[PDB]
Image (cartoon, rainbow, N blue to C red; front, side, top):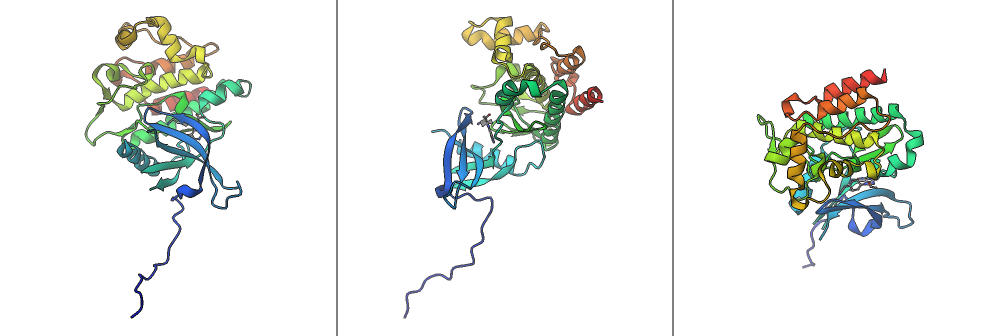
Length: 293
Ligand SMILES: C[C@@H](O)c1nc2cnc3[nH]ccc3c2n1[C@H]1CC[C@H](CC#N)CC1
């Protein structure tokens, strides 16, 4: 008799689903090698009132971004950037937008407001985020100031997980294959030499990130700048080897100006050449807390 259609089942609204047609690009926020993040307004009413979100997509790998999304989705911590959702057909990760941006952007513009005490609190907060990540059996592999987002003058959050990887149960490390675009000047020796990644490797990276925090992410003070000073800036493809050598010799980044030795000693506990000799995120927390009392 009559044209048979399907009975429409009552459609809910998934608050973690962002319709592409309503996601309006405002501007670029930053990139990785294969990923990029844009500021957008999710503006379903079309009057520029919608919330601002950070949208992560692939540069023209889908499986790695899906993995990153599964990681972020199930991380619940105040020092971890918030998952808001996804936008699907292909996929985009939707996160909270932090207007102060990363430490690289915020620190140089707010030096006057940010004293050693606030920096130690950030450092504490970065350790708590990382420790949490470590308890989820993840290694981050990209801990640097550019990935530490400023929520407020009193709060930072780890704001990217493009390189994050689970470590198998009953295993101490993750062996990486693709290492082309490694942040070598943030990387522990075991990473630079054997492509192995421990939680301890992230402790090393934190030391370098802490050093960035302490130099207010000044570009002329970056671990890359300073390292290319110690080893030479014109070794091309021998750079990494020259790096591993220097580190073998016991050379590390120098103490930041106006950084008390006691803070610098916690930093150097991070840069123990052997992973088993490095401090842990919880000991760093205890250390920093000690300095704040
Ligand atoms: C300015 C830039 O550092 C920045 N501002 C942000 C505000 N909210 C955000 N939410 C998620 C990222 C993010 C933000 N990012 C960058 C953080 C690192 C990221 C690295 C990659 N890909 C690129 C965006």
